[PDB]
Length: 125
Length: 125
View 1: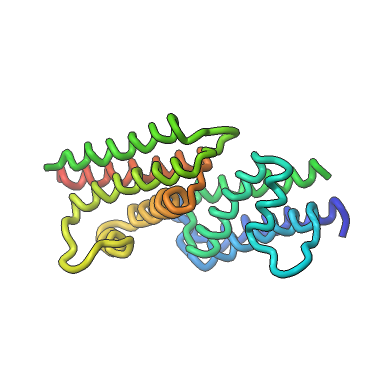
View 2: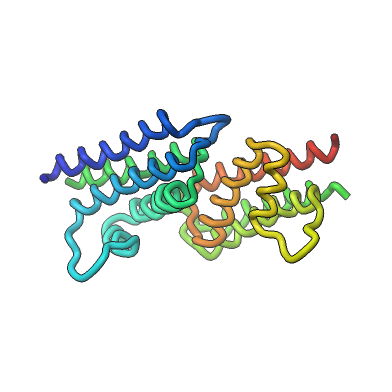
């Protein structure tokens, strides 16, 4: 993969996640009621963010890549984007992917934050 | 009495004041986690204060999140989901992890006022 193919794929995970919420999330009264699809959507969107960051940054020697690894790298580049990322981690990786909670307005914001990180990577590119 | 509702709102507004005065907001993120945590805990404790006054007492042990959820499930599902989102945003993301995405925090606080108004509005039934 290359600069822009990597960023395109990242954006496809995002749109796949939005598609999942739209089609299977069961939005009623501002909340996605079907928890398993909130988790799937959150995990997929988060993975899109990590795909973009995985390419934009580097490959790491010695062991698994956790939230800290991403935090270090962003913290050297752009504090706004780091903060945006920690917010995406909280909203997509923990609230959605782990807890299964889909407050639709909060989710929309969390995806806006993920798209900001993808579009950042693409701009820096 | 049911100035339980007023005291709940004092916690919420105190929480907003702490973020304004000590949260260190920058580029849309509160930079000082200490105060994000404090604000979150205070706002969340406000909501619990209104709830504790409406639902009263649990016969054995201490309350936790499951006690509030099962009490709210018997009452109304929109309000259940609203409270879960409060729990996610104010108790987990802010109070515990110290993450303050100001736009997201605002929604969390709107959800909290929704719950306090629901209490006020049931108690005057």
